[PDB]
Length: 376
Picture (tube, rainbow, N blue to C red):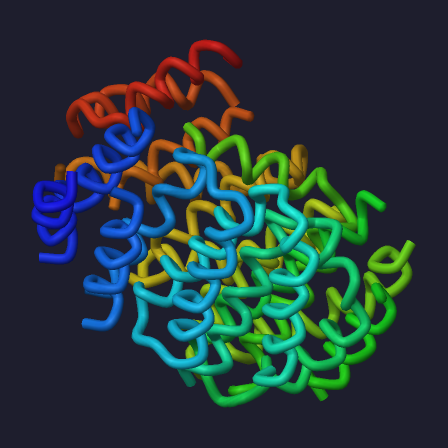
């Protein structure tokens, strides 16, 4: 009970590590209690990954009520202020599993974390974002109690000179603005467009991406399915002209900006579908030859083909020659995903089969060829 559990928990810190945390939950479901509190403290202070695996897994297993929240809150509150990568995001998941238990302390515990996150907003700044993102998923009600401080504090913290924050801080804006839609939009577009007028490019474009995508679910529902295999409408010409001017100018200026361009180009075209399309197609086709953007280039090209139906048919001979040249040598996991969305145009796919199958058996290929025969 005590000695054998402490030995198996030591192996989690030192595939097999997550299995011991799952086996500890299976053994704890059958059930001593004091030694598990000491065993969490033994692994905590030294290790931090194996300690989070022990604490977070036993929540929603044994039956932790009032005494368990007060103890384990102190461990999570110490990790978040300053930590390394990977350990930070696991510690933020440990908030979410504890916070969705449905106890009386949830009102106090969540609002303690949300209020302290606004003070910070770099291993400090990105931590507050991971707390706010994970609490928005797990606890929708008590996260809505501080929305006006949320939007105002984040537009100060986003524009600090960092890349790791820009990826996560827009995901906090994603988790917050989705809660507004189901139940602010002017304050997002006003403060974002002020920022555009290379640190002030790739962050603004990701913030504008949220306003295009939430306003029109038609853009995301094409993207969500292929992966498995008023406000924005008013300032459409203002947002589209600023992004197209930013994309056409910044061709080889500063990997990150080219990645955010290929995210927006299809989602802006899916909002409102020739000169905008012709400038898009020149940027997309040229990005395929270059590496880094080669994965995202076909993804944008696949989204654009479904949204823009008739006008894309002129650029079929250009795209299909690149696909016919890319496959013969055998990265290609995305190549198959976009050929399914290209049909979503029939006789040309018959010639595409003799290299497609010659690549080899992959989980992407047989997922595609099955869903290829469904639609056409």
